[PDB]
Each structure stands twice: as C-alpha cells, then as structure tokens.
Image (cartoon, coloured by chain):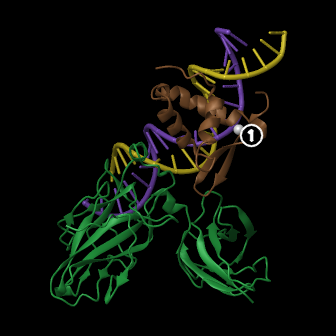
Chain colours: A brown, B green, C yellow, D purple
DNA sequence: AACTATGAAACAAATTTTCCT
DNA sequence: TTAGGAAAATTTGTTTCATAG
C-alpha cells in the first residue's frame, strides 16, 4: 500500500546480503519481498517479473548452480559500479 | 498417551529390544496427488510388501507400530513436509490400520501382535504428495520442495517397561523416489559393494541401483566442513550388458597419499547434467 | 541526446500437476 | 482400483521493446 523507496536491485541485494549464507534461491528472494513490505503482497505477476529481470541483467547478480538447483549471490565489487 | 516429537532422534534398538526391518521398500514409487486416484501401497522389490519386526519384546500384548513418511536428505531425520503416508483399506489389504495426526505429519498406526511374533507386513501404506505452493507458503516452513522428491518410510514403536518407563525405538527405511519423472531420468544407488580402502585404491567397487546407462559416469569428491569443494576425480566406470542393474567402478587414488588419518569422501553418478544421484559415503584409509 | 529504473512480453528448458484410458 | 503416459501448467532465466525522468 506504499511503493517502497528502493530499486529492485537494491532490495534484491538486501534480501541476499541478509540471509544466513549470503545466497538465496529465487523463491526465497520472493519470500523476502513478500514478508518485508506490504506492497509486495499483491500484484506478484508484475514484481516477480521485475525481480527475475533484475537478477539476470545486472552482472552483480550471479547464479551459482548446485545439487539442489541454483542460488543467487551478489558480487560487491560489481554492485559497487554504476551506482 | 506418550510424548516423542517426530523430530527427536531415536536409536533402532535399546536393551534387549530391536526394531528390525526384514523386507525393504522397492526403489521407485510414484506418490499420488489429491487431484487423482490412489496409487497403492509401497510394494517391495520381491513383489510383496515391506516388513518390520520387533525382537526383545517377549511379553504377550500387542503394540502399536507407527508409520510416517520421513525426510531423506543429508541432514538428520524429520517428517517430510511435502509427503504424507496415505492409508489404504479393504480389498487388497490385510493390515488393520489406525490413522493419527501429529503437528502437520500424518501418522499411520499398525498393530504388531504376539500371534505373528511382532512382525507386521506393511501393505496398507501409500504416499500422498502435497502441492509445493501450499507447503512452502506456510507461515513458518523454510523447507525447499523443488527437486525435493525422495522419502524414507519411518517406523516407530513404544514398548512399555514394567518400571514405568516408556522405551521408544525407531528405524527408517531406504530412500524411495516418488517423482514420476525423477524415476525415468535420475540414476540411483541402492547398494554399494564396499565403503573404503587405503589411499591407494585400484580395488573394484560394485554399485547396485537404477537408471544406470552406458554414459553413467561416477565422480568422487571431497569438501571441507564449510562446503567448499577441494577435490574432484572422475573414477573409472565399466559396462556390462548381461549384468542388469549394477555398475563396476575402479576406486581412484586419493590426492594426498601421504596421510596419517583416515578421511571422508563422497561420490555420485551422473548421466547428463541434471541427472545426478545423491552423494554417497566412502572413506580412504592411511597407507 | 543518452541513460536508468520500470513495465510488459516473448521464448525456452526444467519441473510439477492434472487428466485420461 | 492401480498403472502408465502424457497434456497442461508453472517456474525459472533470458532477452526485447517502450516510456518517464
Ligand atoms: Mg546476472
């Protein structure tokens, strides 16, 4: 009910850099937006799309494949460029 | 009347008692979804059904033998929040069953009676699969669910002791794969010929499992307590057409041959890329 | 004039659910 | 029933265009 004053990248970066091992599966990043801001508890079709897009396009977000699927991580020296 | 949270560890035996597991469940078994008919009980490799039996109980009075689908991942044992044991009845069933429910885990109680020497023939246990979106989206549950489709038939019993002490015993089965697809594609290792040797190797180890193909490669690996892999060797595997579901691999040689303490290694099987078995246990001993 | 953060989509490949027989 | 098989859907990732600031 209030568009949080942060960019997706900023938040996607926060959810990750706050989890126990600094890495999250896509669904878990979703679970972070959802329980962190009431704004994300609606219109999922739209922001979920936005997150998947931010996660691929920005190089500071690297997908690390593993046995249990794949997790997302942030590369600080990179997130610290162009912003 | 008792109190043993399904998540609490329990040995398979204590005192003169032992909760055996005569026959074992077969490898594959496609759980059924609420939106579909039943898919029967868990059959055995033989063609029959699993079988569990007590031992140290020599008194004469039935006992309730519990049953719940447990988890089968690396971590300790715990109820598998995505799978529920499902009670089958009537026609093709010869085991009277009682159906409880603890927390969020469905439990199926079967009786073990002195008449059959405390030996029940689990032929009424089925497996129901819950949809993931409904289980992950639970206020507390932080468990995965995607590609999370292997289970273990967990058995538990409470022998009452004449001292006023409830003695709990429990034992899990071998992992079963409930996914239709992850049964046609993912190779699985049911039994391994040997579990160790000197840092030398060369010795052959036979693997018995499923979906083993002409491209089934095996790989040994090692990793620290944090998860960082520090070794990756591709053990040499063979090909035998007469031999149906087995694999013959040549234990590779450990990296540091100059070790004074035994180590822990893991090995799996890979048919393509996504098609990869679980990590199997193995140990290299000092020269 | 060129960017950026956002929206809205097209597509592909891996997986999960639902229907049929 | 129970067993098989597979169509339907969804999930997860990639890319394309467009527009407001
Ligand atoms: Mg990226």
Disc 1 under 8 Å from ligand 1? The reply is no
Of residue B157 and residue A65, the one placed in the foreground of this image is B157
The residue under label 1 is A76
Residue B225 sits above or below residue A49 on the image: below
Counting from the top left corner in percent of width and height, residue B271 is at: 63, 64
Element carrying mark 1: helix
Q: Is residue B22 visible?
A: no
Which residue is more in the foreground, B91 or B282? Answer: B282
B138 vs B91, left or right, is right
Above or below residue B25? Residue B198 is below
Left or right of B72 on screen, residue D20: right
Residue at x 38% of width, y 67% of height: B8
Q: Position of residue B173 (x, y in %)?
A: 40, 74
Disc 1 chain ID: A
Q: Which residue does the image show at 60% across and 32% down from the upper left?
A: A51
Q: In which quarter of the image is residue D21?
A: top right
- Would you say residue B146 is visible in this rendering? yes
Which residue occupies the foreground of this view, A24 or A68? Answer: A24
Work out which quarter of the rendered image holds the C terminus of chain A and state it. top right
Place of residue A60 in the rendered image (x, y in percent of width and height, measured from the top left): 73, 38
Nearest the eye: B37 or B195: B195
Q: In which quarter of the image is residue B68?
A: bottom left
The residue at 62%/28% (across/down) is A8
């Amino acid at each position: 009910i209030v568009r949080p004053p942060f960019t997706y990248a900023t938040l996607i970066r926060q959810a990750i850099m706050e989890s126990s091992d600094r890495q999250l599966t896509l669904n878990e990043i979703y679970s972070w937006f959802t329980r962190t801001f009431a704004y994300f508890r609606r219109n999922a079709a739209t922001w979920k799309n936005a997150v998947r897009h931010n996660l691929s396009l920005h190089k500071c977000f690297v997908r690390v494949e593993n046995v249990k699927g794949a997790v997302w991580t942030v590369d600080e020296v990179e997130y610290q460029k162009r912003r | 009347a008792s109190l043993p949270p399904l998540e609490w560890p329990l040995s398979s035996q204590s005192g003169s008692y032992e909760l055996r597991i005569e026959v074992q469940p077969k490898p594959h078994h496609r759980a059924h979804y609420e939106t579909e008919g039943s898919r029967g009980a868990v059959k055995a490799p033989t063609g029959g059904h699993p079988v569990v039996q007590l031992h140290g109980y020599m008194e004469n009075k039935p006992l309730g033998l519990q049953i719940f689908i447990g988890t089968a991942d690396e971590r300790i044992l715990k109820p598998h929040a995505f799978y529920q044991v499902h009670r089958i009845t009537g026609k093709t069933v010869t085991t009277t069953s009682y159906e409880k429910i603890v927390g969020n885990t469905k439990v199926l109680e079967i009786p073990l009676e002195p008449k059959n020497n405390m030996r029940a023939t689990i032929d009424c246990a089925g497996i129901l699969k819950l949809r993931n979106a409904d289980i992950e989206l639970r206020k507390g549950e932080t468990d995965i669910g995607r590609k999370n489709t292997r289970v273990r038939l967990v058995f538990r019993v409470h022998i009452p002791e004449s001292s006023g002490r409830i003695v709990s015993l429990q034992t899990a089965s071998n992992p079963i794969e409930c996914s239709q697809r992850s049964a046609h594609e993912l190779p699985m290792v049911e039994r391994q010929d040997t579990d160790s040797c000197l840092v030398y190797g060369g010795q052959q180890m036979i693997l018995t499992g499923q979906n083993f193909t002409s491209e089934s490669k095996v790989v040994f690996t090692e990793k620290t307590t944090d998860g960082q892999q520090i070794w990756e060797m591709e053990a040499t595997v063979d090909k035998d057409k007469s031999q149906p579901n087995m694999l013959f691999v040549e234990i590779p040689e450990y990296r540091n041959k100059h070790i004074r303490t035994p180590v822990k290694v893991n090995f799996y099987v890979i048919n393509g890329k996504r098609k990869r078995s679980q990590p199997q246990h193995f140990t290299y001993h000092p020269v």
